[PDB]
Length: 129
Image (cartoon, rainbow, N blue to C red; front, side):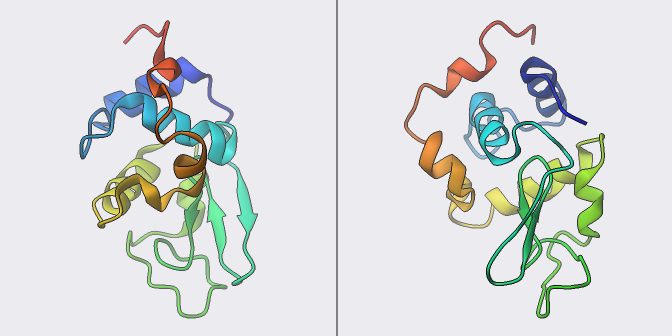
């Protein structure tokens, strides 16, 4: 499912991501935009052989099981395909574990590179929340 900006903002909000760990809603949306272009079906393979899945491009090396990443750790306890659903719940639960892990949102390269330090509030402007 390809989300609309405001639609995603409202779902993430509803899922408790606004200010989760001190990161405002616009950070989350900004990251989704740049990680997957708001598409829950986004997948991308990496050189280490791992793959990134979903709207937040969660990696199979640590976070989910895809059956083809030797040495995966499966920290969120889910199959990676659960991160491609139209229902963002598993993505959100898994993202909260990630962000709580120590480097915060820096875990997301597109976030660090394109969102961090910008006026991320722009991402939820005009939304009915």
